[PDB]
Amino acid sequence: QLQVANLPKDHQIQDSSHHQQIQQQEQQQQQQQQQSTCQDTIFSIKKQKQGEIGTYKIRNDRDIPFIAQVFDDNGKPFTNYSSLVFDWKSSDQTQAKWLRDYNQNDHLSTLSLSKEQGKVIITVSILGYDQELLRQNKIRSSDLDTSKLVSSLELHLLVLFPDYYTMYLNDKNHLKIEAIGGSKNFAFTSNNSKIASLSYQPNSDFVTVIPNQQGYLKVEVRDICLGSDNNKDQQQQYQQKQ
Amino acid sequence: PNHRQYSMIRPIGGSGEYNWYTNNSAIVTVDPTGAITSQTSSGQTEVIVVDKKNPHNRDKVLVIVLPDEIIITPSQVEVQVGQTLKLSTQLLSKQLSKGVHFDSCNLDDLEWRVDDSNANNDNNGGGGSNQERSFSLLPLQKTNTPKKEQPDLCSTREFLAIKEGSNVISVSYMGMRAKILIFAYPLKSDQSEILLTLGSTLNVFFSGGPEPWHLERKSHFQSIVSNLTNEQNVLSIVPGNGNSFRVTCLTHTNPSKPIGIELTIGNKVTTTNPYPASPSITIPYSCRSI
Image (cartoon, rainbow over all chains, first blue to last red):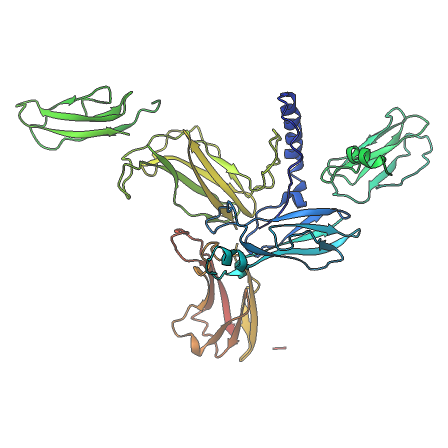
């Protein structure tokens, strides 16, 4: 099977601060609600049947590591399988492209994505056992049914409007603001409810604005399945050069 | 230790009147009728019957109090959306001969679950949306106590198929554990009546029915035949590519013998699917102004 390679983070020292378990459960309960509608995303990979290619939604403009997970046909993953030769492929190397990491034959590989929107199929195969590792151990080759040793995924590559408006102050004069681009799972916020009220429904593309007082409303949006680009920790590291 | 177990020994012959005894009442007690009950202790004991009218007529039974392992008892695992699936459980001991069970099991309180196949990372107490699952575990009713459908069965549950696809089911008790995989699926034609002129020909198409059984696949079949032991003079049936076939007209269909073509799709019985799905559908046929 293909899976996304969730690398470990750095092993920072294990402090025993119990408070971390609360913020882990706060995130797990949010994730359990989000798992109702995140189901189409690359983080929601359901274990495929042999040849059962799944469509998964993914955001463009990034590199992503993948792992080729190998099993026996009792269904156990193998404890080590570093004697097999792998074959990493894409239907279009403009839309999505394997890099030139050192081990182009390994059970791990890195996929670069374009800056576009569109669709591309990724695949991994096994070609056989390495004959040179078998020869060094003096072992005979045994010939693999590689027709059963292929796995594939389809990647689907993926703003408020109006961005500025002038609302005449009357209790009947309401503006619609709509969320162009994202998962269609949105949460809307504003700077000051004393200037205007927001009104929206669950799983709405849009929010309605109702004028309470003169001034400036600002309206903002979070994606429930894709988040928000405000990843400050990486912005701290780049500020020294940028 | 909490769940005392019960059985009944029966005497045959003698003067019709008995006394009962146990050689160890801390392992098993017996009543005046021949019912036996396990007590606080495991191990081995004897239960004895004695004729009242002359105590030389007597006999005895060995009772042993012992388990290792739990299974889900084999049943069907391919079912339609909108139907229920029965699963039961059974206890084993590695002291028993292969093909022998316990004579009775009352252990109904088992830790039955539905498992979700994507739940890899998130150690979080989130109320996950009960919309994405193919299956659900049904509540135990608080109606009158049922008779178990067999006496060796620890517990029984039904699972409702809500959505197409599959879930894993799991069970635990005192560290013993079992699991099974269950599937939610129905079969259809495009054509509802095949009415053709002499020599006319039609292509026919179908959807649903079982996947070739995961582990073996050569156990699968599609089958297409008409309701006459004599077909080759009336119609020609020819299988197509994938879920398609062809019907070619040969001679007139007699109205006092309405013809049906049956399409069957299923898995054959194997050592990995003992109770497979094999649905069919019958399709009406006829050969006959402007």
